[PDB]
Structures are given as C-alpha cells and as structure tokens.
Image 1 (spheres, each protein chain N blue to C red):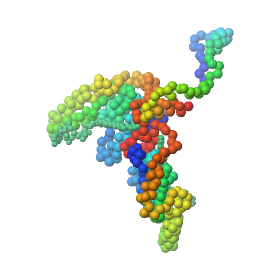
Image 2: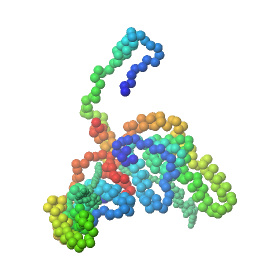
Image 3: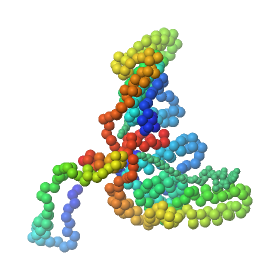
Image 4: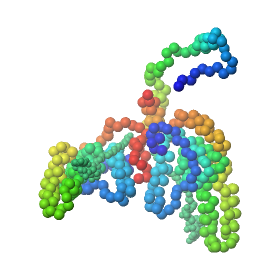
Length: 69
Length: 172
Length: 172
Ligand SMILES: CCC/C=C/C=C/C/C=C/CCCCCCCCCC(=O)SCCNC(=O)CCNC(=O)[C@H](O)C(C)(C)COP(=O)(O)OP(=O)(O)OC[C@H]1O[C@@H](n2cnc3c(N)ncnc32)[C@H](O)[C@@H]1OP(=O)(O)O
Ligand SMILES: CCC/C=C/C=C/C/C=C/CCCCCCCCCC(=O)SCCNC(=O)CCNC(=O)[C@H](O)C(C)(C)COP(=O)(O)OP(=O)(O)OC[C@H]1O[C@@H](n2cnc3c(N)ncnc32)[C@H](O)[C@@H]1OP(=O)(O)O
C-alpha cells in the first residue's frame, strides 16, 4: 500500500535507471533521524501574556497550551 | 453541538429549514425549552463555526442554524438560498387573514401575485447579502474548497471576551 | 440545583420518596434522561450539600436526593427513615412471584411475615448508619440547630480535586 515513484514516458536502460535513482537518492536530504522532538515549555509565550483574572483564555489558551500533548 | 465543542471539533452547518415545526403536540412536547437549549448550545460553543445556507432559511431556522448573529464565524449561501422571517405562503396567509373571504375569486389571484413578488424580492439571498448578514453568496461547486480555506483560517480561533465562571446556565 | 450552584446557595435536601415513577407514560416521557440530568446536576454542584431523611429513601430516590455517595457533605436521618433498594411491598412482590398464585393463604401469610421482617431489618436507618452511609440518626427537634452548625462548618467548602475544562457534558 505504499506510494511508489513512477516514470511516465519512455523507458530508461538499467544504467539510466540506476543513475536516475542514485541522483534522486542523493537528493534525499534531511535530519537522518526524524522523530518527535523533546518538549520544553520553559518561557513559552503563553506564560508571558497578561490575563484578566476572569479571562476565558486562561482555559482555552493558557491551560490548553500547557496540557496539550 | 455541546459534545463537539467539548472535543474542539469545528462545526459546519448546512441549513435548509422552514424553522420550528408548528403544532399543539409539539408545543406540549417542550419545543420552546428544547429550541432554547439548541440556541444556548450554538452560542456557548467556542469552536470555529461555519455555515452554508442551501434553499430555505426561515425565521428561527435561520437564527438557530448558525446565523452570524448567533456567533457563527463565516456565512455562505448558495444562490438558491431564501432568507426571511417567514415563507411566502405564510406571509400570504397572514395577509389573507385580512378581508378573509377565501371563497372569493380574486383573493386566489392576489395571493399568487403576492407570492410571486415575495419570492422575487423578499425570500432571497440578496437582502441578507446587501446588509452583510451573510458573508458571501457562492457558486455551489466552490463549497468544498471554500470550507477548506475557511476552517484553515479559523484553525486557531480564540473566543472572547468571555467571563470565566462555574458554568453557564441553560433552559432546563 | 444548577441555579443555586451558580449563585453559591447551600443545598438542603429533605428526602421522603419511593424513587422514580414507574410506567410506560413516564418512560416515553423521558424519565431516564431527566433522572440522569438530576443526578448530573447534584454531582456537578460545588456548594455545601446537607441532607435530612424523613421516612422513605428507596433506590434512585436515596441516590439522587443528595446521597453521600453522590458527594453530599453531611447526611442525617430521622429515626423514621427507611433506606433501601426497594420498599417491602415491592420486595414482597418479587419474592411471591416465584410462587404460584396466592390461592393458598400460606402465600398471603408468607407475604405478611416477610414484610414485617423487612420493615424491621432491611428497610431501616440502622444499616446505613452501621455502614456510615449516613453520618447520624438524630432526634427530629435537633434538625434546625444542627443545620445551623453544619452550614457554619461548610461555609468555606472548596470542591475538589476537579479538573477545569470548558464544561461538563449533560444528558440531552
Ligand atoms: C459560558 C456561558 C454561555 C451561555 C450563553 C447561552 C445563551 C444564548 C441564547 C441565545 C438565544 C437566541 C434567540 C433567538 C431568537 C429567535 C429568532 C426569532 C425569529 C423568529 O423565529 S419569527 C419572529 C416573530 N414573528 C413571526 O414569526 C411572524 C408569523 N406569526 C406567527 O407565527 C404567529 O401567528 C404570531 C402569534 C407570532 C402572530 O400573531 P398576530 O398575527 O400578530 O396577532 P393578531 O392578528 O391576533 O392581532 C394583532 C394584529 O392584528 C391587528 N389587530 C388585531 N386585533 C386588534 C385590536 N383589538 N386593536 C388593534 N389592532 C388589532 C394589528 O394590526 C396587528 O397586526 P400584526 O399582524 O401584528 O402586524
Ligand atoms: C468541569 C466539571 C464538570 C462536572 C460534571 C459532573 C457530571 C457527573 C454526574 C454523575 C452522574 C451520576 C450517575 C448515576 C448515579 C447512580 C444512580 C443509581 C442508583 C439507583 O438508582 S438504584 C435503583 C433501584 N434498583 C432496582 O430497582 C433494580 C431491581 N428492581 C426492578 O424493578 C428492575 O426493574 C429489574 C428488572 C432489575 C427487576 O427484575 P429482574 O430482577 O430483572 O428479574 P426477576 O427477579 O424476575 O429474576 C429472578 C431473580 O431471582 C434470582 N434468580 C434465580 N434463578 C434465576 C434465573 N434462572 N434467571 C434469572 N434470575 C434468577 C435472581 O435474583 C433474579 O434476579 P436478577 O437476575 O438479579 O435480575
């Protein structure tokens, strides 16, 4: 059920196929280890704001920002 | 609506209604308090609220099905929409309550001339559009991508000003 | 109850009930959800909750009328109280339906004996007092001053631990 690369017009020889795939694999740049980054809420912007003592954003912005995981 | 608000699902309304159902059995069934609870839930919900009006949107149906006045964020109508206090036949009967001799030949003519005028001039998208009660009248095919663009805009909606308190009371 | 909670009034429950109404007309009338909402409101409310039981407290009547298990703070009974899953007559019907029809008066005599034993034992204050489901059995004349003492104690009640959130959902 994976999405495969497709070649739509012409057929390359095995040498041309290897060169095409090899250069595209080289173009596959990135982190080399893509995973969920370490959470660190220290000094998050939502703690910096002034909230009125009765402001509903204390629920729907501040708390949800801290508690969401 | 209250469940969706509790789990932060955006709400999409697809209106096509004459409003509350008339009848003594529905009156005795609590339709005022049940409708008031529906009105309460729509206003209480903090999630993004987007509305598309298809065809009829009369009276309380217009109001309760996510009108802009009841805090809907973006309001669209198809060109078939019909926004009014009451439908043409109800307005006609409300006029024919005066000089009410419905056996007469001409009253059944002026009824149809009134209904024609009312469905051309009143029960349409265009007064709500020109007053800005709805934000756009759209070709129907636009709807799917319009809803994507809208809910992407509203993704971070913060509702306020609201006063935090133990809870909001509701008709019960 | 929800109104009193919103305006911080203490709640006093005075209990004398066989519980929910039986019957098809009340079932179709929605008794399951309306009782569910009553249970919801009583558990939701944060105010002081004080209960006095006069005679009958059967089944859901006991539970819903500010039971300690539903977070009531202080619970008292008069010595006339009867706290049970069902009253003696109901338990006698469930017993006797295991026998044939009462054509033999031994069946009637068994009902009468069972009902007296049940009203001496199961349907009394004393089991709930022995288990601590109610905090005291009181002489009726104590009630007024004991309510004063109790609500002076409870004046500063803080209800918790409760997790703040948009709202608690309600049977609708
Ligand atoms: C955290 C915390 C958060 C919590 C927050 C939550 C809270 C938020 C909650 C949010 C709440 C949301 C609220 C949404 C509001 C609902 C939407 C409203 C729109 C409608 O949904 S819909 C408007 C209403 N409207 C019709 O429908 C017209 C159609 N109508 C009908 O549906 C009925 O039928 C009826 C009864 C209404 C019409 O009644 P009637 O026809 O008016 O009455 P009648 O003829 O008996 O008498 C008067 C007439 O006759 C003449 N007349 C007779 N007798 C005399 C006399 N003695 N002297 C002088 N003149 C007389 C006179 O001139 C007059 O004229 P007219 O006809 O009034 O102009
Ligand atoms: C941010 C903050 C937000 C905060 C939000 C907060 C919100 C939260 C709120 C929270 C909300 C609170 C939720 C609620 C609270 C709890 C309330 C519940 C307590 C009650 O409200 S409590 C009622 C009283 N409770 C009965 O009447 C039952 C019994 N009374 C009845 O009237 C019933 O209608 C019925 C149908 C059950 C009686 O009828 P039956 O019992 O079904 O049948 P039967 O007696 O004819 O069967 C024969 C019997 O003999 C035995 N037996 C021997 N052999 C067999 C056999 N082969 N097969 C079957 N049985 C057998 C056996 O004992 C059997 O009985 P069984 O098998 O045990 O049933």
